[PDB]
Length: 121
Ligand SMILES: OC[C@H]1O[C@H](O[C@H]2[C@@H](O)[C@@H](CO)O[C@@H](O[C@H]3[C@H](O)[C@@H](O)[C@H](O)O[C@@H]3CO)[C@@H]2O)[C@H](O)[C@@H](O)[C@H]1O
Ligand SMILES: [Ca+2]
Image (cartoon, rainbow, N blue to C red):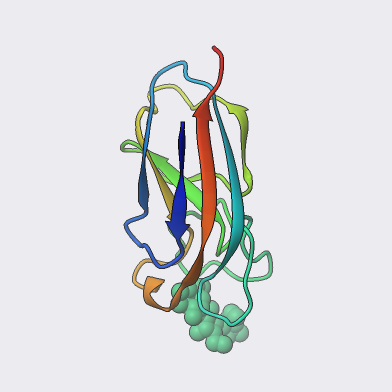
C-alpha cells in the first residue's frame, strides 16, 4: 500500500510503489486542492467548466487526478477508485498525474494526497 503527494506542477507525474498485476483489485482515495493556473483551486475531479485545450487525459476535467499503469494511456482517478479492476493487458507501475496540457505545468500549484492499496482478490 502506498501513500504520497502528487504535485500539480509535476508533468512527468508521481511514480508509486504499486505495480498493478493481472487480476489485481485496487482502491484509491485522493484528497486536496490544486490549480492548473488560476488563483482558485479545485479538488481531484478538476474544473468542470474548463474546455479541453489538449489535456493528457481527455476523459477527465482539467485539474483532475489521472494515472498511467505501465505503458497505458491515461485513466481517470478523480476522487478515487473503489475495488477497481483494470482492462485486460493493462499492467505495470502506477504513475499518478495531474491532468493538464503538456508544457503548461509550470504555472500549476498545490497537490493531492493519495492512498492506493490492493484489495482481496
Ligand atoms: O487549459 C489548460 C490551461 O489553462 C490555463 O490557460 C487559460 C488562460 O490562459 C486563460 C486566460 O484567462 O485563457 C484560457 O483560455 C480561454 C481563452 O483565452 C478564451 O478566448 C476562451 O473564450 O476561453 C478559454 C477558456 O477559459 C486558458 O485556458 C492555464 O493558464 C494553462 O497553464 C493551462 O493549464
Ligand atoms: Ca497550467
